[PDB]
């Protein structure tokens, strides 16, 4: 039979907000992970799907879920450059100073990418310049 968690990951990545809600109401685990540890929240945060990020969080998504590389959804939003998603993640308790496998924080990632508005937001939320 079909895997609801795999469908939830695909709906979160595709930006299908109606399907995300339906899947979860029918038993899809909000914290379903693929082979690399990516959750629906990691995918919605990467693809810039703000409403899906908010829906996932309201349904109990782990805001600080880490994949095999230690990337939290905040790392992914800061790297790509989704400002409103960074702000929503921080509001829901994202670890501003989370360090991935390469020793990078969301602040480092936003800085190297030249995402200055995100840099300022992270710093205002307690990003440690020495982490």
Image (cartoon, rainbow, N blue to C red):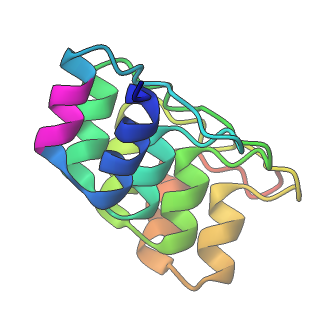
Q: Residue at x 71, y 67 (%)?
A: 108
25 relative to 13, above or below: above
Chief SS of the magenta region: helix
Segment colored magenta: 18-23
How many numbered circles does the render carry?
Answer: 0
Nearer-the-camera pick, 50 or 109: 50
Q: Is residue 86 left or right of residue 11?
A: right
| Residue placed furthest toward the left | 18
Q: Nearer the viewer, residue 31 or 103?
A: 31
Left or right: 64 in relation to 50? right
Which quadrant of the rendered structure holds the N terminus? top left
**Picture quarter containing residue 38?**
top right
Residue lying at the far bottom of the rendered structure: 114
- Which residue is at a point 58% across and 32% down the rendered structure image? 64
Where is residue 66, by image quadrant? top right
Residue 83 image offset from top left, x and y in percent? 36, 65
């Amino acid at each position: 039979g079909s895997d609801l968690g795999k469908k939830l990951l695909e709906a979160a990545r595709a930006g299908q907000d109606d399907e995300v809600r339906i899947l979860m109401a029918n038993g899809a685990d909000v914290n379903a992970t693929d082979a690399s540890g990516l959750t629906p929240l990691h995918l919605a945060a990467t693809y810039g799907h703000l409403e899906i990020v908010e829906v996932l969080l309201k349904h109990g998504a782990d805001v600080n879920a880490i994949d095999i590389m230690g990337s939290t959804p905040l790392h992914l939003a800061a790297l790509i450059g989704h400002l409103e998603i960074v702000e929503v993640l921080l509001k829901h308790g994202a670890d501003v100073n989370a360090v991935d496998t390469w020793g990078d924080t969301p602040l480092r990632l936003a800085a190297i990418m030249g995402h200055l508005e995100i840099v300022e937001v992270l710093l205002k939320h307690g990003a440690d310049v020495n982490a």
